[PDB]
Image: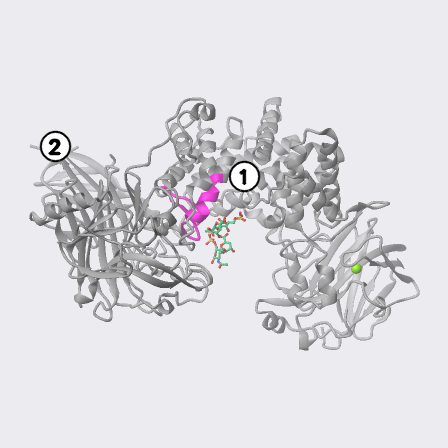
């Protein structure tokens, strides 16, 4: 407390706090005849004393303090977010009081004299009170009196008060509770309950007790975002620092507990130096509950009976202090928003300490408390399945905490009802196809958060959802097979699109820090061992491969010999992210487009700032292993030159997202993505269309970009390339990788190039091999630039300068001012000898491939090495072709004539939905030349031709094997 008024316009954000650790601490206070005010060091919140107020019913005391109460608009301008001036204090009751305390605000008040509010006194322990002075009183500039009036209908009593504070707070976070009513309320959980009920039986109770033990086993025998401490010396040292002591007739003294979000009410950055020093003695709840967990884990593992007893006493004392500090049912503590960050390991600690809380008679208090603060999570914790139930962050941050809370329910019948309902909730969450862009799994195996396929969020959700299924396995509470099947699809998909990191195109807003399947490994064991017919040999074989374990090691893990999965081979279409994956030997190629339903990039205030081209028809090649070790190095990376993309080469100031905060740029039509044939061949169709009027986006930048992938090779073609400036700085990147001692060699036309710097220009019939063994044969280009150069770039978070040496090659489209084009072929197993053979084959009337059409309506590529034809119908069309006559929608078609059969696949990569609507299936009529007979594809001979009817659901290709009719 200073001599200045609260909310001093001159220093609006500086809190005024009565903590009584200063000179003449009751200077500003006076009492009527019927009240006595003492300082007590028996308990306190801030500094070592609190106000002891003894009273008869109806007696007041007055705090004399000038308040220049700002409007909400003034407070919000001073801070820069929606704000309100708040009055807050802490009070302690040693016994409950059947009545209300009245707090009145006015000018020159005494016991017998504007606005005010009431605090119900029927409780024990510390409670916090926090009200908006503008919004929560039942305030003219001249307020100088705050009058605390003891209840009129209670003959005597006594209350401890501390830390009376005037502050500017976030306008969202003064919550109602059992003591104070505010304009804001977080309603309590109302648990859903599924019928029929499971009975309390010895079998059902044992299954419950087994689930709890299985959770204990997972937390005592390595979690992300858990600060594990197994050293008892360290645990007792951190505990002793808390200075917790049991008090005489009940409660505790010890350092004050506050959450990371609660501190906002202080505006700590603006505290005067006296106040800050006291505030710095607080303990952050996250750290305290982490200590409770590490102690509970040490207790469970501890062999020495004396140490084991000490760990238990430490855990129960920390529990009693936590409850006495007002973390109990009905105590909002003004707010507990983002409760999970502060409490997640408290929930888990109760599993380990469940018998110890039972014996100490704390289970019901701790359950009531955790249930109350969980009300923040009522949308999930109520356990009614809804469109939002497939939340991927929930699976990561909250699902095991939720199960722990249910297991802490003291009644047996209720506990069984809650866990039965939980099993139903998790089954629905893992089974349902959420509408539109909502979080969750999808039928092609993609997994969505922030309204798109997002491995950075899905990978942690896979790990914990697999663990949940495994914890409930082989009990009456086991997750339904439909949820197991869907999660299997998503996790086998993740194995296909990672190597073992997801590519740059799947990195979301963290390019060059891709999630790795290595972090999800244990999930494959947990899902493999929770199969109806366990172990699932596919998931078990993937666990062994991703965790680098041998066939020899398999019997002990799975109870039978399982060969570690070899890397997946062939082509897989994932239109949930308008991508596909081509795999050959140890290489993965991520082919990525974008469209109305697939954002190109997530760009935030400090994330992925130069990410505009992340999905621009990219084709990133990755060998099994570290992408950094293959030269995907952020430092000096030219953000314009994403492998395979057609881009405008911009200065980074113009490539930077035009929005200062968030942009998730969606495309201009539904159609763009991939398709597959026989699980082996693929095609990408990318319609590059820019917005009519977005700053820094050339509205006339266009391209049609197709790729056909088969076996060791990919054929890349482009047409209809344009910009506002005759294709000036328009480029297609063949490759870009750092130069290192392991990545030092390029081959050009049989010559090894190692010099740095180096520039040259190549044309049709030339070839290159990058340092990762990818060959590029130029089959149509006027001008391919190759560069080994020092590059200056900037890092994607804070735009700070970076530099590095890179090998790259790109096509310069400026030589063709209108409707520029390209063709080139990649060999994934290139050697100088093999590239010499491919170049000679290309020179023999192109024995490699044939483009049968390349225009704005259709791209048709015949691969003569694989004998496969890909058809990208950018528009519906009739064509001239041996196989395909007509396609009535934008679609990707693929054919393979083998001996006695024609195999035809078809799909539209268009998901046929919005951010709100469920995807519905698209009917595609594909007419083929000639008479055929035979898959859910329908066929009908119609004159000399055959009509195929495909159903394209969520961009999932269908195919049919046809044989000729006489
Ligand atoms: C606040 C912000 O920039 N973006 C919002 C998202 O917040 C980010 O994502 C998450 C997260 O758990 O997903 C936590 C952090 O606040 C921040 O990194 C998020 O609030 C989304 C909504 O998610 S979605 O319903 O899945 O779309 O909205 C973003 O703009
Ligand atoms: C896509 C995304 O930001 N996802 C969030 C995580 O961020 C990724 O992973 C990590 C990391 O070390 O975990 C760091 C980078 O921010 C990014 O590659 C991460 O912030 C977690 C935090 O989880 S929480 O504390 O465990 O609940 O949330 C991710 O899913
Ligand atoms: Mg104090």
The extreme right residue here reads 33
**Residue 478, how many percent across, how many down?**
51, 30
In the rendered structure, the answer to whether residue 889 lies left or right of residue 14 reads left
**Disc 1 crowd, CA 10 A, few/some/many (<14, 14-19, 20+):** few
| Vertical relation: 339 (above or below) 726 | above
Range of residues picked out in magenta = 438-463
* Residue in the foreground of this view, choosing between 242 and 931: 242
Q: Which mark is residue 899?
A: 2
**Residue 714, how many percent across, how many down?**
22, 47
* Residue in the foreground of this view, choosing between 879 and 543: 543
- Which of label 2 and label 1 is nearer to you? 1
- Is residue 163 found inside the magenta-colored segment of the image? no
The residue carrying mark 1 has its beta carbon less than 8 Å from ligand 2: no
| Vertical relation: 415 (above or below) 715 | above
In the rendered structure, the answer to whether residue 169 lies left or right of residue 801 reads right
Q: Secondary structure at mark 2?
A: loop
* Residue in the foreground of this view, choosing between 98 and 861: 861
Which image quadrant is residue 564 in?
top left
> Upstream in the sequence, badge 2 or badge 1?
1
Q: Which mark is residue 222?
A: 1
Q: Residue drawn at (28%, 68%), measured in percent from left and top?
A: 699
Image quarter where the C terminus lies is top left
């Amino acid at each position: 407390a200073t001599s200045n008024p609260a909310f001093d316009p001159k220093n609006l954000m500086q809190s005024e706090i009565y903590h009584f650790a200063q000179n003449n601490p009751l200077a500003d206070f006076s009492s009527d005849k019927n009240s006595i005010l003492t300082l007590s060091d028996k308990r306190s919140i801030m500094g070592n004393q609190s106000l002891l107020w003894k009273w008869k019913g109806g007696s007041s005391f007055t705090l004399h303090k000038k308040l220049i109460v700002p409007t909400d608009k003034e407070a919000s301008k001073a801070w820069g977010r929606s704000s309100t001036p708040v009055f807050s204090f802490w009070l302690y009751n040693e016994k409950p009081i059947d009545g209300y305390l009245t707090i009145d605000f006015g000018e020159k008040l005494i016991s017998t004299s504007q606005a005010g509010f009431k605090v119900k006194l029927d409780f024990t322990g510390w409670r916090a009170v926090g009200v908006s002075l503008n919004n929560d009183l039942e305030l003219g500039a001249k307020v100088d009196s705050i009058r605390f009036k003891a209840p009129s209908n209670v003959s005597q009593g006594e209350i401890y008060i501390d830390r009376i504070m005037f502050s500017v707070d976030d306008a969202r976070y003064q919550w109602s509770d059992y003591q104070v009513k505010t304009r804001l309320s977080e309603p309590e959980i109302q648990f859903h309950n599924v019928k029929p009920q499971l009975p309390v039986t010895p079998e059902n109770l044992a299954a419950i007790d087994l689930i709890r033990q299985r959770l204990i086993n997972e937390f005592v025998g390595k979690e992300t975002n858990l600060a594990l401490e197994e050293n008892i010396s360290k645990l007792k040292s951190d505990f002793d620092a808390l200075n917790i002591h049991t008090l005489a007739n009940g409660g505790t003294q010890g350092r004050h507990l506050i959450t990371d979000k609660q501190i906002i009410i202080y505006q700590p950055e603006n505290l005067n130096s006296q106040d800050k020093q006291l505030f710095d003695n607080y303990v952050i709840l996250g750290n305290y509950t982490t200590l409770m967990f590490n102690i509970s884990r040490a207790y469970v593992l501890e062999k020495d009976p004396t140490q084991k007893a000490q760990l238990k006493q430490m855990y129960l004392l920390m529990t009693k202090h936590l409850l006495d500090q007002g973390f109990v049912k009905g105590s909002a503590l003004v707010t507990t928003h983002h409760w999970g960050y502060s409490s997640r390991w408290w929930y888990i600690s109760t599993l380990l300490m469940s018998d110890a809380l039972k014996e100490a008679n704390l289970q019901t208090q701790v359950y009531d408390s955790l249930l109350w603060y969980s009300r923040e999570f009522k949308s999930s914790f109520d356990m009614k399945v809804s469109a939002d139930s497939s939340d991927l962050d929930y699976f990561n941050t909250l699902s095991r905490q939720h199960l722990a809370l249910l297991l802490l329910e003291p009644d047996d019948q209720k506990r069984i009802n809650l866990v039965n309902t939980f099993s139903h909730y998790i089954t629905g969450a893992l089974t349902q196809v959420p509408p539109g862009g909502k979080d969750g799994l999808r039928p092609d195996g993609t997994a969505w958060r922030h309204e798109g396929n997002y491995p950075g969020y899905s990978f942690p959700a896979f790990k914990n959802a697999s663990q949940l299924i495994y914890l409930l396995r082989d009990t009456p509470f086991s997750v339904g097979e439909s949820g197991w099947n869907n999660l299997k699809k998503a996790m086998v998909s993740a194995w296909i699109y990672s190597n073992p990191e997801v590519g740059l195109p799947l990195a979301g807003r963290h390019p060059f820090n891709s999630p790795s399947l290595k972090s999800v490994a244990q999930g494959y064991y947990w899902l493999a061992m929770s199969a109806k017919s366990s172990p699932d040999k596919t998931l078990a074989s993937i666990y062994l491969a991703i965790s680098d374990k041998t066939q020899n090691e398999s019997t002990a893990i799975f109870g039978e010999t399982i060969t570690p999965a070899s890397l997946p081979q062939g082509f897989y279409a994932f239109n949930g992210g308008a991508f596909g994956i081509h795999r050959w030997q140890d290489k993965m190629v991520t082919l990525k487009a974008y469209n109305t339903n697939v954002w190109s990039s997530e760009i935030y205030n400090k994330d992925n700032r130069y990410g505009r081209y992340q999905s621009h028809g990219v084709a990133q090649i990755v060998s099994n292993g570290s992408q950094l070790s293959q030269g995907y190095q952020q430092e000096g990376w030219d953000w314009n030159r994403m492998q395979g993309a057609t881009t405008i080469h911009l200065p980074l100031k113009d490539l930077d997202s035009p929005k200062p905060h968030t942009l998730m740029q969606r495309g201009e039509r539904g159609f763009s993505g991939t398709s597959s044939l026989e699980g082996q061949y693929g095609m990408m169709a990318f319609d590059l269309i820019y917005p009519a009027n977005l700053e820094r986006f050339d509205p006339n930048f266009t391209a049609k970009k197709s790729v056909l992938a088969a076996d060791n090779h990919l054929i890349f073609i482009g047409s209809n390339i344009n910009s506002s400036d005759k294709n000036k700085n328009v480029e297609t990147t063949l490759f870009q990788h750092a130069i290192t001692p392991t990545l030092n060699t390029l081959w050009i036309n049989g010559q090894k190039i190692e010099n740095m710097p180096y520039q040259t220009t190549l044309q049709q019939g030339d070839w290159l091999i990058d340092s990762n063994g990818n060959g590029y044969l130029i089959t149509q280009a006027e001008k391919v630039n190759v560069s080994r150069q020092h590059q200056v770039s900037a890092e994607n978070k804070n735009r700070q300068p970076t530099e590095g040496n890179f090998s790259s090659a790109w096509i310069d489209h400026s030589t063709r001012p209108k409707d520029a084009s390209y063709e080139y072929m990649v060999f994934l197993d290139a050697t100088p000898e093999k590239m010499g053979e491919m170049a000679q084959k290309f020179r023999e009337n192109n024995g490699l491939y044939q483009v049968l059409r390349k225009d704005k309506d259709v791209h048709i590529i015949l691969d003569k090495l694989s004998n496969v034809t890909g058809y990208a119908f950018y528009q519906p069309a009739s064509i001239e072709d041996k196989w395909i006559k007509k396609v009535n929608k934008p679609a990707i078609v693929m054919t393979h004539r083998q001996k006695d059969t024609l195999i035809v696949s078809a799909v539209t990569p268009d998901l046929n939905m919005t951010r709100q609507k469920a995807a519905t299936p698209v009917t595609i009529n594909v007419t083929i030349n000639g008479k055929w007979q035979s898959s859910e594809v329908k066929y009908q001979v119609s004159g000399d031709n055959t009509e195929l009817t495909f159903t394209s659901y969520f961009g999932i290709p269908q195919e049919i094997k046809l044989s000729p009719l006489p």
